[PDB]
Image (cartoon, grey):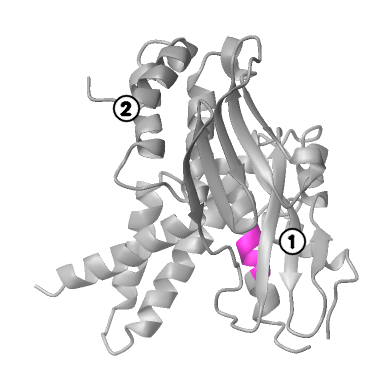
Amino acid sequence: NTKEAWWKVLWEKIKDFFFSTGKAKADRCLHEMLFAERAPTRERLTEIFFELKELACASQRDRFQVHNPHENDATIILRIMDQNEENELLRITQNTDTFSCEVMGNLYFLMKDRPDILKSHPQMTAMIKRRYSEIVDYPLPSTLCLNPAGAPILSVPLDNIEGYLYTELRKGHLDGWKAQEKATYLAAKIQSGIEKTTRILHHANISESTQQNAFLETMAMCGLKQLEIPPPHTHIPIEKMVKEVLLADKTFQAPSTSQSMLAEIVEAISDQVFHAIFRIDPQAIQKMAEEQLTTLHVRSEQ
């Protein structure tokens, strides 16, 4: 045994929360989370939390609770309680600029990341607050926070989006739309990555062939298949879904860079919503697609 003092004490108390093969995995989770060479990203922080919840038996799943203190959207906390709800075993808080984690009441770390979905825009900041959504069993983008340079901070909520899922809850039962959105969204991401890397690498003559080979190859690795002809129109995608709930607020500003800023906002919220649902990072996929294109190309060099 080479565990930490607070780890052994935590494990001895959480240990029985998981079945057979499940504890070896929940053990590596914890390790990545609090005892690795470095602290996880906040996004990776939240994932690990649910991998644990998902790994624990249903009996102990009510032990994994998440809420916004006094409905204070600016902050969110995830935690693992004890049987008699006697105190907190693991506490994770996430504010607007930092996030921390406590183990048995001990502060293990406070990291500071740079939440700004409008990175490509200097004179503009925008973050995304969020609250737990049991329809996806994960926190999802609750409200969008903007901070222009010349006007007060905007707090346009986006809780209407969760509705599109509740309305689909009882209908052609959303379980189906997930198979659609998953392929549509991801394949589109794979295509952007392709066209993107091709532009910057324009000086390199990357055949339209390789371009298609990469697209089919990454689609294959992800397992999904293309059958979007046509996209059963009676299906409102996440983008259109979010584009809606936005304009639904008198947010509408006439300063100027809109076609680019509004398209970015949308893409950031959609990605996260999407990630909230499928627990897949749409950007991670776009990257592996970009790497496929380059890897294939350098292969056709010989």
Report the magenta residues as a range: 265-269
Instruction: Please state the horizontal and vertical placement of residue 32, each as a whole percent of the image.
Output: 36, 38
Regarding residue 209, the answer to whether it shows in the image is yes
Q: CA distance from mark 1 to mark 2?
A: 39 Å
Q: Nearer the viewer, residue 122 or 85?
A: 85
- Asked whether residue 34 is drawn in magenta, I would say no
The type of residue carrying mark 2 is: Glu
- Coordinates of residue 198 in the picture (x, y in percent): 36, 79
Residue 268 is a magenta residue: yes
Extreme residue toward the left, this view: 302
Q: Is residue 109 left or right of residue 28?
A: right
Report which quarter residue 168 is drawn in.
top right
SS class, disc 1? strand
The spot of residue 39 in percent (x, y) is 40, 47
The quadrant of the image that shows the N terminus is top left
Q: Work out whether residue 245 or residue 15 is closer to the camera in this orientation and state it.
A: 15
